[PDB]
Image: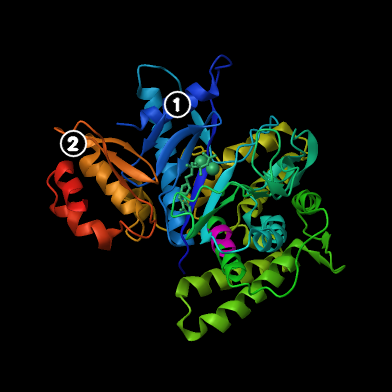
Amino acid sequence: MHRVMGIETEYGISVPHQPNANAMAASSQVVNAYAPANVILTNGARLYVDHAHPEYSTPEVTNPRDAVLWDKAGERIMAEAARRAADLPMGWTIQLYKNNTDNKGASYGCHENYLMNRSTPFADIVRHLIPFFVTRQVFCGAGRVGIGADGRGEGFQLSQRADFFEVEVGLETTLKRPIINTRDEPHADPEKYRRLHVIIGDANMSEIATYLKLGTTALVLAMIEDGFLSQDFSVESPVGALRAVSHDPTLRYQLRLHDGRRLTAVQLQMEYLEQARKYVEDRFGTDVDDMTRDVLDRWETTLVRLADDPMQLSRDLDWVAKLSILEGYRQRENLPWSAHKLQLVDLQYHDVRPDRGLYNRLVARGRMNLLVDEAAVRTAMHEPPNDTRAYFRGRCLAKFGAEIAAASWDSVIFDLPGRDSLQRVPTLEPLRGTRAHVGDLLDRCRSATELVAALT
Ligand SMILES: Nc1ncnc2c1ncn2[C@@H]1O[C@H](COP(=O)(O)OP(=O)(O)OP(=O)(O)O)[C@@H](O)[C@H]1O
Ligand SMILES: [Mg+2]
Ligand SMILES: [Mg+2]
């Protein structure tokens, strides 16, 4: 399938035995440790400090798989960065967790960006997106021990971010956290593209969960752009139903719909599913991508698997995988969900360290289904996507990085010796500046000045 998307994960950061240490500082020390604080990677990825958290923004990708690949790559990058921070003269040993909460009452988001037609009514987006985002935590939920933002509430939930959203629509602020974020920063031609900023998702360790999160959403976004959805999935008290779903790991609870019909999160997801199948069949027909049908079947299988038993998905889904780890401890040690150990286990699951990370052990123990190979994940660290402008950005920093004064999604600003003014080549088109467009040019160009000349 093809959708221009990206995943910006704000990594949970902690400094052991460092009450004095500042998040902004620790978050910066790690981002600066990888430099050899906004840093653009050869990956086309972005490393920077955001909200006092180290953040990794994948390069722009055209599919949920590559998004998975370059997000995962970000984990390896975060781990490496944190290790280097300890190697630096500054002694800080920084723990990084890919998670949405520190269980202290603080919540940092894993953002998913999608490129949509600007012509797509935002009202239709909100209408059909809200119900989807509320109920997608079934597979997407990283899982969280403790209920409510404070986490003092005894229990296990699907979503780590669910308790942190008061409002359904609006701009994301420090005080309020909307389900549907109103911020439009396309970083692409504004008339042609709208960048949908999805803040409601939990950062997933599981490659499948991320795949489904991005894939299913991408599907739903397609139907919204084609105005395919006839019905209204809108839910009364979506923000409440959001938490409700998260708060029920059994997924028994049904949402109340403005049409009056009652459906569980999974049933509602199935509604989107068959609608998604019905949409792709109508449009794609036989030409449908393998990945589109893969996301389709994985979405259907998951929802069916979920309905029958959640735990059979323990290899695929974070919240189920974690729940597996958690229920084990509980049965073995007879611990209530109020047990602090369960929270440490919840947190440790997201630990970026290969040895310490519970998800990472599961992967090493073969307890998780991977959608991508570690060999590719490694390459995806220094190597950008070929199908996106990230290629031009990434390759430039690698070869021309020395001559580059600044880079972003919007452009790459070179400094050419002999030119008093900085030369800016904007990457406005996410789909341009790919391996095909700039690939040869970047191979031939001996210098940035030579490259800038070719582009001009
Ligand atoms: N045109 C686009 N369409 C879809 N996704 C995009 C686009 N441009 C960038 N992205 C994605 O957005 C992420 C970069 O987001 P960034 O960390 O800069 O946050 P932001 O969008 O500036 O907002 P904030 O700084 O408030 O989080 C990348 O992971 C990338 O994949
Ligand atoms: Mg960001
Ligand atoms: Mg963001």
Q: Of 319 and 354, which appears nearest the observer?
A: 319
Q: CA distance from mark 2 to mark 1?
A: 29 Å
Is 416 placed above or below 182 here?
above
Residue at image location 48% in from the left, 21% down from the top: 25
Q: Where does the image place residue 177, in percent across and percent down from the top left?
A: 69, 41
Which amino acid, mark 1? Ser
| Residue at image point 67% right, 60% down | 129
What residue does disc 2 label?
416
**Mark closest to the chain's N terminus, 2 or 1:** 1
As drawn, 203 above or below 437: above
Residue visible at 75% across and 32% down? 150
Q: Is residue 179 magenta?
A: no
Task: Name which residue type carries label 2.
Answer: Leu
In the image, the residue with mark 1 has its CB under 8 Å from the nearest atom of ligand 1: no
- In the rendered structure, which segment of residues is drawn in magenta? 211-217
Q: Is residue 9 above or below residue 321?
A: above
2 vs 1, front mark: 2
Q: Position of residue 406 (x, y in %)?
A: 32, 36
State the residue in front, 269 or 120.
Answer: 120
* Residue that label 1 marks: 28
